[PDB]
Amino acid sequence: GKECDCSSPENPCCDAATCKLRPGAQCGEGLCCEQCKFSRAGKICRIARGDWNDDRCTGQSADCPRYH
Image 1 (cartoon, rainbow, N blue to C red):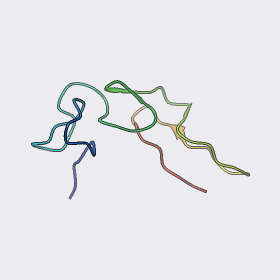
Image 2 (cartoon, one colour; image 1 turned 180 degrees about the vertical axis):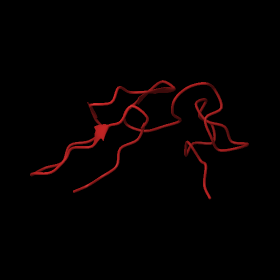
Image 3 (tube, rainbow, N blue to C red; image 1 turned 30 degrees about the vertical axis):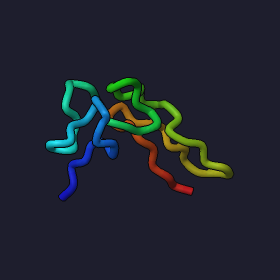
Image 4 (spheres, one colour; image 1 turned 60 degrees about the horizontal axis):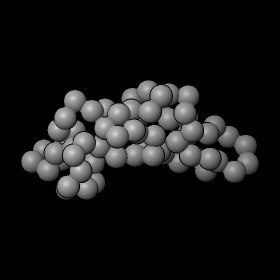
């Protein structure tokens, strides 16, 4: 599988030995993740352009997906 919580091998929020959150933070990298923390759900992890469901950052998500 793949547990690379982050993509940077120098990030303090993740770990290179296991490519995953090293500290007790809540994320290694994303658009809705404070310095080692999960933003608050109901947040905007992106901005669609016409009609659909925005990428409301979840209370357990740090990056942002994409529907359109």
